[PDB]
Length: 166
Image 1 (spheres, rainbow, N blue to C red):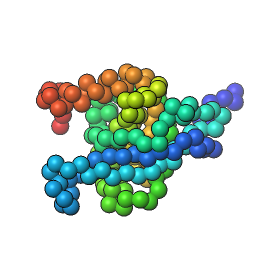
Image 2: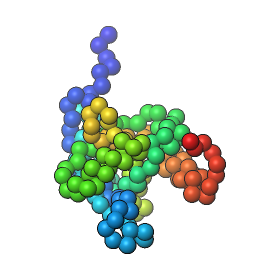
Image 3: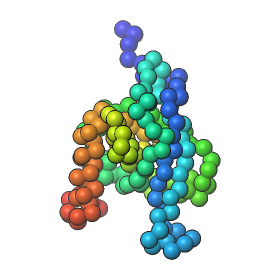
Image 4: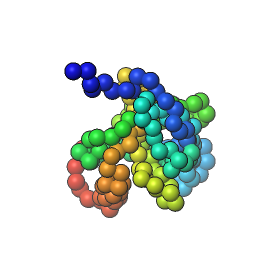
């Protein structure tokens, strides 16, 4: 009965991109209305045996840091998702540590594939591994459902709908 081994052992580089995001308004400029845009180049690994259709994947993605439990609240729709491992390189040290700071604070990140080529994958979710101290992203198998679902959630938050918040 030999079947059921997760082929995450041998990791294949299938794509590399950079996440560009809004940094926290830390004293450096006007701060208030200034979008400090920092970015970390990531190399993304997949599992062996399969392949990822990364010819639909750009090398710059807009990543939005959002509360981890907000994702937990969305949950079931992305129960089955493929784990893509995001290995970052040293570029913005402030932002690297602050990304580490922010995820550790209780964050995940919305990886948005620009509305120009949202071919299959339109939004992807970044999370932090507490054990591997690296970042991992998940490609939900309900891609459009994730996007609309997360958008309604973000709208629910910004419109001020008092629905689940400690």
